[PDB]
Length: 7
Figure: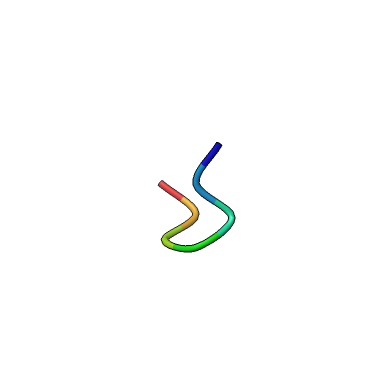
């Protein structure tokens, strides 16, 4: 999902 932002 967002393993860029986390959230």
